[PDB]
Image (tube, coloured by chain):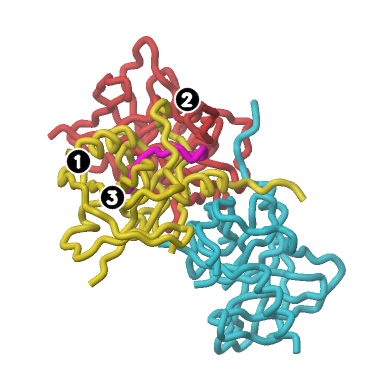
Chain colours: A red, B yellow, C cyan
Amino acid sequence: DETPASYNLAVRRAAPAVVNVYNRGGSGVIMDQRGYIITNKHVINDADQIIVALQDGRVFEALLVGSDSLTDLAVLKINATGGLPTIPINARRVPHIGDVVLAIGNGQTITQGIISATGFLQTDASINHGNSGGALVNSLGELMGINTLGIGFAIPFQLATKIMDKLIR
Amino acid sequence: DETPASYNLAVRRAAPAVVNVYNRGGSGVIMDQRGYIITNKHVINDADQIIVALQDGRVFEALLVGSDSLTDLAVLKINATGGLPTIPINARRVPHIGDVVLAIGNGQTITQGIISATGFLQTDASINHGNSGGALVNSLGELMGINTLGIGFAIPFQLATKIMDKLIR
Amino acid sequence: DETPASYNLAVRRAAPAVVNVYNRGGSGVIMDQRGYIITNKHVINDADQIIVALQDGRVFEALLVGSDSLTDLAVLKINATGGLPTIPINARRVPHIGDVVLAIGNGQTITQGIISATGFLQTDASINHGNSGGALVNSLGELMGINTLGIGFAIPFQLATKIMDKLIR
């Protein structure tokens, strides 16, 4: 009949770029075409072998670029091939309180909510060990933050961008 | 003044069809005019007498048509009278991830959320023993699933439709 | 680029009027210019000195006007100065089930949800000891209720208005 209210647009626009992290004898986000992926520290602590899994079926072995114990963030590196799904980033967008946000983690689950505060970034979107290290995007799909660990916490994409660049030293 | 953002439309369109189940010395959904009602198995296990209560005030004694231990579903039957409120069904609607959904259970409570995954159907709408067996509809009121038992689970209306038809054997 | 789905409008329209309550050796809401503030009883029980903190930075010492053990409500009084941010009230608005609502409490956190029932007022917006006594507004910012203590509870603004007026005796 008509159009059901949905945020699927932001899903098919951001979800592809979110991956799953594993250990061969956690969540992650594809930042740029170079193949850099932001995740969490507690996800890679004592990692024998880091593995990345895309939604399209592709599987990679990830390289630990570096981590930051302060913000619990970590950067990974995979062999950038032809055609990588990257997380939509908008450095001009200013996260206002009340903005609708989706939390993308892991089975690939999508929770809905809003920006509670911007003190870090608080959100009422269901966060857990599954989506810990996943993405946080607005209705447009623009990355607002990186989920961390009755209210959830993420790291502003602005900050995460900086920290990522510094870990590449 | 102006119009407050609301999903009341889907409420006055689906809520009437959702009923309450009891035992005379759980939730349920009115499917068709014939008087068939889908509920959960754990709701009728060891039932002395099944009772159905509509939102309009009408009260009925329900008949156990049959259950399916696999999907935890059950079908009831009440004497179809003149004028039954049926749950809006749309077999053409395809549940996409990110779609806004309401969870209708039981006091008649309405929780809001989205479709997390479609693996079953995951949703961040608050689900509990109250709405266990209730309806799950989009902003249009179209039945998306039947709630079951930090993330909730429902059964695709497509599947539930089949299983219901088979229990009528 | 474009416009991200958000309820920030209701925030910059209601949040200023919500304050924080303290005890000098809880949440509250600025009702009118006179300086009357609605809060919860359990927040002021055994209070040595009641203190009110606005979002603009202003700090006041509050006066206990009176409380109502029944609805767990309480009314405070501060020296009404020039220019007070008051909570948007609309006595003509009728709270329908399914309406989008924000819960404003305390760091100043904003949770999103809907009106579940209107029996009291039920809401799936995350409520806790933080926002206990805070505001509950629709997408327009119009006060729908006062939060109290897997589902949250508030008091209809219609009722709270009456009880407030009676405590001023």
Q: Position of residue C112 (x, y in %)?
A: 54, 52
Q: Position of residue C47 (x, y in %)?
A: 59, 87
Disc number lying in front (3 or 2): 3
* Residue drawn at x 34%, y 12% as measured from the top left: A81
Near-viewer residue (C147 or A102)? C147
Badge 2 density bin: few <14, some 14–19, many ≥20, Cα 10 Å:
some
Q: Is residue C138 above or below residue A3?
A: below
Residue stretch rendered in magenta on the structure: B138-149
> What chain is tagged by disc 3?
B
- Residue bearing mark 2: A13
Left or right: A38, with A95 as reference point: left
- The tally of labels here is 3
C-alpha span from label 3 to label 1: 12 Å
* Residue drawn at x 59%, y 47% as measured from the top left: B6
Q: Secondary structure at mark 1?
A: helix
Amino acid identity at mark 3: Lys
C-alpha span from label 3 to label 2: 45 Å
Amino acid identity at mark 2: Arg
* Residue drawn at x 41%, y 25% as measured from the top left: B92
Badge 1 density bin: few <14, some 14–19, many ≥20, Cα 10 Å:
some
Left or right: C34, with A71 as reference point: right
> What chain is tagged by disc 1?
B
Q: Secondary structure at mark 2?
A: helix
Q: Which mark is residue C67?
A: none
- Residue furthest to the top: A82
Q: Earlier in the sequence, mark 3 or mark 1?
A: 3
